[PDB]
Structures are given as structure tokens and as C-alpha cells.
Length: 50
Length: 100
Length: 51
Length: 112
Image (cartoon, rainbow over the protein chains, first blue to last red):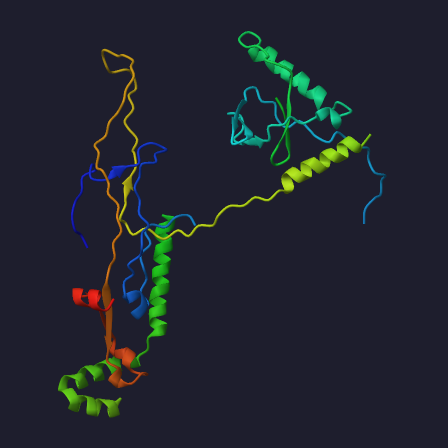
């Protein structure tokens, strides 16, 4: 379902072929309960070659 | 099955792989490091020079090295640089011999 | 186009799995259960023996 | 004599037979808390357009967002409900209901 719009200026650009200043986190999945109660499939973004 | 033949004669222990026109050398962490734009590998070696004359009694490595360094020097460096001293030999990790 | 077709095939297999995992009696049992839960304790007292 | 060739084989073998290793990595899937965008191609001119061309040195500054990282703790309770009165062999036809709810402060301090 739809929610809202964003400007191209609202997201940081990984401009140069090398840059080290990114401040990432160790992401922790908050899995939905339906994955266990009714064997539903979890999203994983677009398909890479592997 | 196969046709039999006697064992063939011996050959030089090492073969020339690359002639590098420009190679930078630096000292770090008690070791030498070598690098060039021609090849993406970085060679690492101990600070002590290897005594090539103890093993290359046939001069099969030594003669070829001298000739190559002179060809390269005459082609590109003779008009803009000078030789600092005599050649040096080093055994790099992975089993390579470098003449510098 | 390749990834578009791969996602179309895994949708077809999911529809096949849905058909073989389920069975015709599920609709009947659901229809009966929906009737019995509508009259409380008496509904359960009859529904448990009917099932 | 072959003695020099033989010891050179030994030195070359020892230099490559040495131990070497690298670590393994566990890569947890990203949740979307940090996202980035990429650059795009530009309409390149066919011939020179501009006036007053000149050369120079430059330094580029960007706005300082000053990120602040810290540690936090979450608390919640998962709940599931199903009509088991139909019997374990038939209850699945009636389905399951489920929810996720917050934990009150009293339970966090007095029990957890």
C-alpha cells in the first residue's frame, strides 16, 4: 500500500567510487508472527544473480 | 599404455615471468613492499638480501636479469634518471624471486 | 525479463501447493464450525459430537 | 652441480608451504534503517558551450548532520488464539488469530 513521497535530496548519495564516512548499524530482524503461525513467506527485496 | 623414452635433461630452476619498467619499493613493519601499475599483486619480503651466487652457478637467472634491466634503462630512463647502485635479489612470499 | 519470469513460475507452484495441501472437507468443517460457535455453550455441546 | 638448484627448490617450497588464513562472516539481512542512492549519467555536450574558462584549486564542504549512536532495549509480548474445542485434528480448519502488544512499566521493573 502507498504512503508518501520523497525528494531526491532526502536520501544520502554514495557519490564517489570510494567513501568511508557512512554510519551503519547492526540490523536485527523483527520477524512477523505469520511466518510461524501460517508458514507465510518473508520479503527479501529484488533478486540478485545468486 | 604408452611409448617409453629416457628421462630428458635438466633445466634452469626459475623462468622469467615479467619485466617491469617501473616498480616502487617501501619499508614498513620490518618488511619490504613492492608495487607497480603493471600487475595488481603486492610482493612482501624480509629486509635481508638473498645470496643468488650461492645457487645460480650457471648464471641462468643472473645473466638474463642484467640484460633486461639494461634494455629497459636505455629505452626509457637513460635521458632522465641515474642508477644508484648494483642490482639486488629478494625472495618474496608465495615463491617468487625479484631482481631490483 | 528473466527475473520477471522466475517470479511468475514461483507463483504457479504456490497455487499448486495450495490446492494439494487443502481438501474438500475443509469448507464443510468451516461451515459447520461457523454455525455452532453462534449459540455459545449449547453450540459447543452439539458441535463437539457432530464433528 | 645440482646442489644449488636443489636448495633453491627447498627455499621456494618453504616460502609457499607457510600457513595463512582469513575470517568467516555472518551477514544479517538489512531492515532498511540505513539507505543510499546512486549517481546517474548526464547529457554530454557535442561541442564547447561555456565562456570565461579557467583553472583552479578547490575544497568542497557539506552540511554536518552530526550522527549520534547509542544502545536501547525493546520489550513486547506475542499472543496467539485458536478454537481447540473442535479437537486437535479439526481445529486447523477454524484458523488462528494473533497479535503483538507492549509490556507495562511495572512488569519491566518488578519482574524482568
